[PDB]
């Protein structure tokens, strides 16, 4: 009666059930087993050809093992053929299949990454022991440096040798005014971009002043002394150091004059630390301009600096000591001479996996591209379908060879048959890195079609062949012109432009399709000089019409007056007309530099030209501050994917900044390292990381420790998630602690820097506070002693969540976006307090999240304040819980914080379209600030099923919130408290709308990463509707209200 | 008729109607101008803008202008294809004028679609794990081979030193010396035998893996074209209805 007695016959019940923890796999300490047995047998191969097998402990150093081996070898024959043990080193084959020599004999058996448990004894070849700490490099990298040396490809070899230009330059800037500049690299000043202060910050200062606390130590290394100043906000560290020394050294035994003289001898012996972490104030910015100060002002805190001896600082900086590595056709025939069309011979795909029943026939689709296509897309015939497919036909492309632009690319795809459907795909650069038009035969191993792409061809996809051999390899052949065809010099292109210009000046009275040429003269029409800036203001995703394109192209020379139009102009050039392109090259040559946030568009997939991308990098070189770079560093690392060649300007820009500023370097390493599993970028990012690692100085050794820590945690959780699943928390937690107590973990997980922030040191592990959270992903809650001198002044304990299992990079981006929305709001005076807690992907679905102390999910609020019997939870309990925390005048401020944070997180969320909010993913801190966690999919990715103009409200303010927002009324909809709130939401909504270009562009730049939520520009197009960019701002306000009203049902007009 | 027009709809939802149609397909649509002819050409959408007349050259209406260019190419107006495919969903939806039963069909197809999208997602993970598992198998094979070399070298290494230490002193020790030297050697060589057997056993596993890998791609490719048509039909059924935006969500 329930199911009409209809049987499901296939259904049989002997990871939907327990639906969590998807990404795998990763092998640990020995091949095929995660953690080696505590006691283990290792064959030691001796130089006398004997195998003696020691039983060793898992945790034992090679010093211990050698020492025992050479005791135990005595008992075997041919002992008199051995030297003293000191004349030997251990070698073995590792899991990366390389024979590593083990130089550092303090290393433990579990930490060597052996393939099989065995150790060959040898006298050390390669007499530069020093040099073969390339092992250090390929640890940090996660692939051995020897794997690059045997790459044939000259581009790679050329990258490696030529990139050192950049390293050697950066290392020079460091040892320039040493030791100060070394300190400046290592400890660069953590500083807001603007010295100007928002209105609302200034007004916490009583007429621009701050009480501060400078601290000092005298003898031995114990007692400390405050010196509680009240300086001007905009006074530099040197001035602040004076006043600490003044007050420290005022006396009844010193005259006024005598004091001034004891100040000057002391004043520049010292520099300012931040108590509790390794941050420092080493250059003349206003105190207010350092981030720590400005935080302290907002949080209502008295800053706690420390007076530090420069020599006790310059003590701690070791020398960086850079070393150059071991790796140090007669003018051809110009592309413009070649008198033919392009034709490409498709030959034969080999490895095509298709059901001959299911699929009728298969062919090779093709196209020439430049982001968009410079000719009609063509296929070939549907020949030898499915069973062993082979077409030996020249495809014929209607474009002359000289009209191929520098950044031209072939994009192809094997398809199935309107039954049209892609199997594989792959793209090739028609020009190589040496500017050489491609000729002869090519093997191209193809990529599988990803999730979001239903399209036939995929040209945004990475240029180059798949490294995975066993995949559809479609080989092919390019025309030959008895010569290595090459792309013209700039000199040659300049002339052709200067000519093409003059030639336009004699074209005559009438031209139908004025379109591409002015016919205006030096005087343009005022209605049009208004229509151009009108175009310029529009966002990148408001596509341009052919009228508008031709129009922009005609007035290209006036477009120099309005530099910001450039992105639009460039997309109106016909890249299949070298006449037009050559002219554009001469504009871009001295086009006025533009704001980095506008220039960053020009390094997305829609601007593949080298000259354009150059200009962009030149913009960044001028304007983009070391502050603003490290914000957008994610998008800039991503955007490398769209560079045609290994060696380019963008790479050389970043690599240099990374070696110039150790704080950038830190995140640069991790962001590249993060994506090293992904074979689209493995080689490229590997090569780059090798450069950085080779040139970055001591930090390599620091990174190596952070890297060793993460690997241990990766292993530990991999066991908890496999074979310790279906065990009680009790049993798991017992396993966890047992393991963390072993000396190798104690070694590896204790003295290092948080990758979330290398300013924080991580000291000893407090295992009593380390635990596995209740999630099925088995995340670790880890806790470390802050081993600063002034732990107490900042935080005695540092705790961060390690989570093997989830792809942290969607979160990472939304949190970055929030970071930016906050900044935009605040720096244009209006205070909405977002809390972009720290996130960082360090792997393939492996990462770190910042713990925010003293905060709870609403659900805990309600579980705590919930009366027995369990009938219903009370709406007021949030409010009651919050009242219970903030009592007196403190209350009034806590509701302002709640209200200010709740409006920001309403607008941000609605705009971004993050996952529906509810009690287990919204959090409230004791001081009354609200913030979201676990955002899910960010651009409305559950609209990929159904969807269609849903324009959802993910943060729907239930009663709970509304009560709190209007102090404690009933019928909260009708208070000034809530009127004020609404007007925050409207001012916040419009503020983001005026910067909408940026947000589009940040998303545009992230298309690179294989995030399923960002497969193509239409994904990003949600953010248009939600911001209502096609409408007027007054309509947009009303739109936003309309949206906010219907999700709430009354309140908003 | 100028409201109906067999294609006049009146940005984003244009592109998602122009998604995956052929080279020629078109339709017609903020103080910029009036209507916009969004014509698709080889994976990229071309937008053409529009006293009575509807750039320089006498066409009295919006329907006047598009019938002319359905016959003819657009090169003569602006240098760089025709309006061949006026694509715009009553043809095959079981012609159902039953407003409710078209809504039920939407759910059936949308449950099939969403079923199918998981099958496609599951398999894509198996594929990608299996790539990783395969290349980890391949690297191990090299590791084995390199391991073996070191032992093959080792059994060779002793033959030089051991058979220098048999002949120099044959009487001294003799079958006390050379027995316990031969024991070691016979450990060393059958150990090599075990290793080589271990490698072999991985290669046979690698082929069975590479076979399974082939089978996953095969079935991905057989799921894919159904996932498009099942999707495309759902969007035509869902378009026919909207010819009740909030009523849809429960079926969907
Ligand atoms: O653990 C060490 C090793 C010596 C250098 C050092 C400097 C610090 O500031 C803190 C810790 C440490
Ligand atoms: O697909 C498009 O609409 C498009 C067309 C030309 C250039 C870039 C694009 O994204
Ligand atoms: Cl970060
Ligand atoms: Cl948190």
Image (cartoon, rainbow, N blue to C red):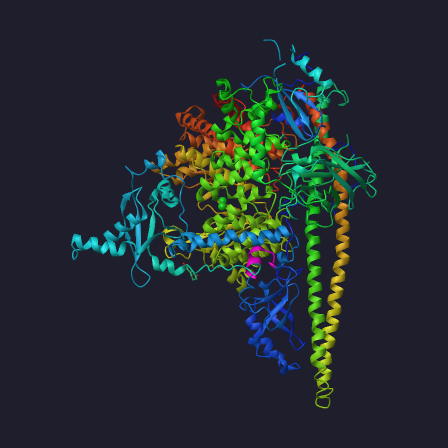
Locate residue A57, reporting x and y percent: 59, 69
The reply, left or right, for residue B252 in relation to residue A556 is: right
Viewer-side residue, A755 vs A688: A688
* The magenta segment: A134-145
- Residue A453 in view (yes/no): no
Residue A142 shown in magenta:
yes
The reply, left or right, for residue A820 in relation to residue B174 is: left
Viewer-side residue, A669 vs A801: A669
Locate residue B217, reporting x and y percent: 75, 44
Residue B210 shown in magenta:
no
Q: Which of the 4 quarters of the picture holds residue A73?
A: bottom right
Viewer-side residue, A157 vs A80: A157
- What residue is at 75 percent from the left and 65 percent from the top? B196
- What residue is at 39 percent from the left and 32 percent from the top? A829
Viewer-side residue, B246 vs A318: A318
The reply, left or right, for residue A180 in relation to residue A714 is: left
Q: Which of the 4 quarters of the picture holds residue A372?
A: top right
Q: Given the current orientation, which residue lies at the most extreme bottom position? A: B171
């Amino acid at each position: 009666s329930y199911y009409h007695h209809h049987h499901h016959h296939d259904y049989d019940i002997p990871q939907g059930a327990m639906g969590s923890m998807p990404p795998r796999p990763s092998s640990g300490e020995l091949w095929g087993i995660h953690l080696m047995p505590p006691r283990i047998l290792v064959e030691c191969l001796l130089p006398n050809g004997m195998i003696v097998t020691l039983e060793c402990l898992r945790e034992a150093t090679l010093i211990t093992i050698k020492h025992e081996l050479f005791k135990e070898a005595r008992k075997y024959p041919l002992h008199q053929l051995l030297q003293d043990e000191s004349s030997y080193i251990f070698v073995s084959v590792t899991q990366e299949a390389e024979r590593e020599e083990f130089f550092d004999e303090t290393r433990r058996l579990c930490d060597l990454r052996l393939f099989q448990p065995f150790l060959k004894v040898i006298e050390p070849v390669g007499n530069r022991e020093e040099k073969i700490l390339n092992r250090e490099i390929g640890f940090a990298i996660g692939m051995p440096v020897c794997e690059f040396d045997m790459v044939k490809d000259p581009e790679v070899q050329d990258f490696r040798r030529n990139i050192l230009n950049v390293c050697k330059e950066a290392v020079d800037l460091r040892d320039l005014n040493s030791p100060h500049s070394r300190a400046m690299y290592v400890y660069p000043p953590n500083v807001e971009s603007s010295p100007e202060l928002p209105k609302h910050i200034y007004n916490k200062l009583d007429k621009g002043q701050i009480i501060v606390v400078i601290w000092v130590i005298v003898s031995p290394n114990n007692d400390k002394q405050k010196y509680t100043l009240k300086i001007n906000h905009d006074c530099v560290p040197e001035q602040v150091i004076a006043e600490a020394i003044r007050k420290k050294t005022r006396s009844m035994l010193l005259s006024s004059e005598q004091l001034k003289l004891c100040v000057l001898e002391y004043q520049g012996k010292y520099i300012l630390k931040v108590c509790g972490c390794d941050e420092y104030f080493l250059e003349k910015y206003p105190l207010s301009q350092y981030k720590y100060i400005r935080s302290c002002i907002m949080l209502g805190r008295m800053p706690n600096l420390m007076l530090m001896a420069k020599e006790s600082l310059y003590s701690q900086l070791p020398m960086d000591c850079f070393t150059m590595p071991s790796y140090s056709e007669t003018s051809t025939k110009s592309l413009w001479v070649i008198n033919s069309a392009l034709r490409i011979k498709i030959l034969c795909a080999t490895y095509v996996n298709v059901n001959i029943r299911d699929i009728d026939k298969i062919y090779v689709r093709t196209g020439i591209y430049h982001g968009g296509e410079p000719l009609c897309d063509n296929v070939n015939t549907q020949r030898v379908p499915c069973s062993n497919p082979r077409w030996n036909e020249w495809l014929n492309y209607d474009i002359y060879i000289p009209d191929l632009p520098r950044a031209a690319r072939l994009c192809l795809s094997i398809c199935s048959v309107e039954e049209h459907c892609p199997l594989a795909w792959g793209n090739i650069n028609l020009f190589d890195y040496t500017d050489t038009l491609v000729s002869g035969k090519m093997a191209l191993n193809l990529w599988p079609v990803p999730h979001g792409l239903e399209d036939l061809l995929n040209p945004i996809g990475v240029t180059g062949s798949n490294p995975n051999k066993e995949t559809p390899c479609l080989e092919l052949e390019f025309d030959w012109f008895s010569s290595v065809v090459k792309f013209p010099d700039m000199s040659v292109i300049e002339e052709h432009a200067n000519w093409s210009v003059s030639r336009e000046a004699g074209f005559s009275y009438s031209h139908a399709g004025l379109s591409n040429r002015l016919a205006r003269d030096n005087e343009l029409r005022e209605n049009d000089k208004e229509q151009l800036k009108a175009i310029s203001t529009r966002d990148p995703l408001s596509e341009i019409t052919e009228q508008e394109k031709d129009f922009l192209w005609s007035h290209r020379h006036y477009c120099v007056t309005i530099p910001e139009i450039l992105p639009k102009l460039l997309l109106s050039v016909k890249w299949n007309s070298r006449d037009e392109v050559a002219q554009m090259y001469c504009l871009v040559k001295d086009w006025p530099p533009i704001k980095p946030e506008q220039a960053m568009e020009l390094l997305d997939c829609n601007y593949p030209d080298p000259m354009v991308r150059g200009f962009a990098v030149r913009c960044l070189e001028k304007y983009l501050t070391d502050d603003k770079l490290s914000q957008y560093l994610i998008q800039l690392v991503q955007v490398l994917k769209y560079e045609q060649y290994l060696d380019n300007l963008l790479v050389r820009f970043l690599l240099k900044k990374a070696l110039t500023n150790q704080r950038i370097g830190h995140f640069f390493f991790w962001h590249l390292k993060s994506e090293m599993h992904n074979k689209t970028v493995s080689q490229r990012f590997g090569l780059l990381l090798e450069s950085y690692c080779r040139a970055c100085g001591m930090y390599l050794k620091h990174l190596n420790r952070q890297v060793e820590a993460m690997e241990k945690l990766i292993n530990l959780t991999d066991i908890l998630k496999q074979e310790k699943k279906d065990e009680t928390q009790k049993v798991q937690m017992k396993f966890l602690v047992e393991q963390m107590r072993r000396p190798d973990f104690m070694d590896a997980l204790q003295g290092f820097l948080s990758p979330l922030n290398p300013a924080h040191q991580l000291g000893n592990l407090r295992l009593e506070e380390c635990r596995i959270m209740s999630s099925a992903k088995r995340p670790l809650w880890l806790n470390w002693e802050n081993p600063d001198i002034m732990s107490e002044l900042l935080f005695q304990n540092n705790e961060i969540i390690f989570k093997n299992g989830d792809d942290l990079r969607q979160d990472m981006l939304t949190l970055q976006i929030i970071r930016i929305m906050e900044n935009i709001w605040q720096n244009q005076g209006l205070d909405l307090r977002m809390l972009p807690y720290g996130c960082l992907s360090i792997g393939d679905c492996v990462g770190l999240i910042e713990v925010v102390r003293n905060s709870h999910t609403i659900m805990q609020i309600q579980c705590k304040g919930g009366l027995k019997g369990a009938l219903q939870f009370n709406s007021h309990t949030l409010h009651q819980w919050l009242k219970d925390k903030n009592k007196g005048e403190i209350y009034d401020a806590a509701i302002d914080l709640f209200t200010r944070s709740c409006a920001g997180y309403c607008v941000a969320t609605f705009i971004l379209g993050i996952g529906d909010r509810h009690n287990s993913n919204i959090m409230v801190k004791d001081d009354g600030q609200l913030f979201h966690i676990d955002f899910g999919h960010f651009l409305d990715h559950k609209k990929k099923k159904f969807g269609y103009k849903r324009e959802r409200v993910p943060f729907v303010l239930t009663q709970d919130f509304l009560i709190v927002i209007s102090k404690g009324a009933q019928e909260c909809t009708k208070t000034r408290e809530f009127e004020r709130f609404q007007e925050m939401c409207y001012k916040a909504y419009l503020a983001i709308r005026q910067h909408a270009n940026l947000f589009i562009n940040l998303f545009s730049m992230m298309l690179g990463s294989g995030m399923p939520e960002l497969q193509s520009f239409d994904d990003i197009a949600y953010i248009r509707k939600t911001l209502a960019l096609d409408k007027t701002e007054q309509e947009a306000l009303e739109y936003f209200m309309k949206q906010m009203n219907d999700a709430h049902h009354g309140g908003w007009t | 008729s100028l409201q109906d027009a067999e294609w006049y709809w009146g940005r984003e939802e244009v592109n998602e109607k122009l998604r995956d149609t052929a080279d020629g397909t078109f339709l017609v649509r903020k103080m910029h101008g009036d209507y916009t002819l969004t014509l698709r050409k080889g994976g990229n959408n071309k937008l053409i803008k529009i006293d009575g007349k509807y750039s320089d050259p006498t066409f009295s209406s919006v329907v006047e202008l598009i019938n002319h260019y359905r016959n003819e190419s657009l090169a003569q107006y602006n240098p760089k294809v025709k309006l061949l495919y006026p694509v715009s969903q009553q043809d095959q939806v079981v012609k159902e004028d039953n407003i409710e039963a078209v809504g039920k069909k939407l759910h059936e197809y949308n449950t099939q679609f969403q079923e199918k999208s998981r099958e496609y997602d599951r398999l894509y993970e198996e594929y990608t794990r299996t790539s990783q598992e395969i290349q980890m198998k391949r690297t191990a094979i090299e590791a084995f081979n390199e391991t073996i070399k070191i032992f093959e070298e080792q059994c060779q290494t002793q033959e030089r030193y051991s058979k220098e230490y048999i002949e120099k002193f044959k009487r001294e020790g003799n079958e006390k010396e050379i027995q316990r030297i031969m024991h070691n050697y016979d450990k060393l060589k059958s150990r090599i035998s075990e290793i080589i057997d271990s490698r072999r056993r991985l290669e046979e596993d690698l082929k069975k893996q590479a076979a399974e890998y082939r089978e996953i791609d095969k079935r991905m490719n057989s799921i894919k074209p159904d996932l498009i048509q099942l999707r495309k039909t759902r969007d035509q059924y869902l378009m026919w209805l909207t010819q009740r935006q909030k009523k849809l969500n429960e079926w969907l």
